[PDB]
Length: 21
Length: 21
Length: 27
Length: 27
Image 1 (cartoon, rainbow over the protein chains, first blue to last red):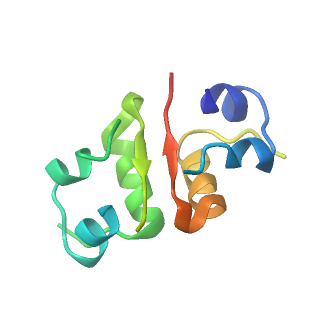
Image 2 (cartoon, rainbow over the protein chains, first blue to last red; image 1 turned 90 degrees about the vertical axis):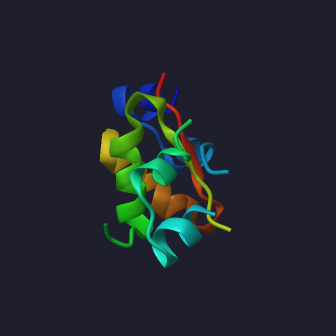
């Protein structure tokens, strides 16, 4: 999930934008 | 939408919680 | 209450919804 | 980059997604 990818790990803009609608 | 109900108008917790998953 | 806009509205949803998370959809 | 957690993660999604909005789903 986003918490796993961006909080526990580090995420870039590409991954963050996957969660935009 | 939420912006209409909570930003343009005023919304309570009940309405805000409608947008929880 | 207050008007809740933009980042304040997002933050309110974050706090209220907790582990459920939320959908923020303008338009 | 940084770790992005909690309200900071929400706020990043808010800024990046703009008018599209976003879904924030822990779990």
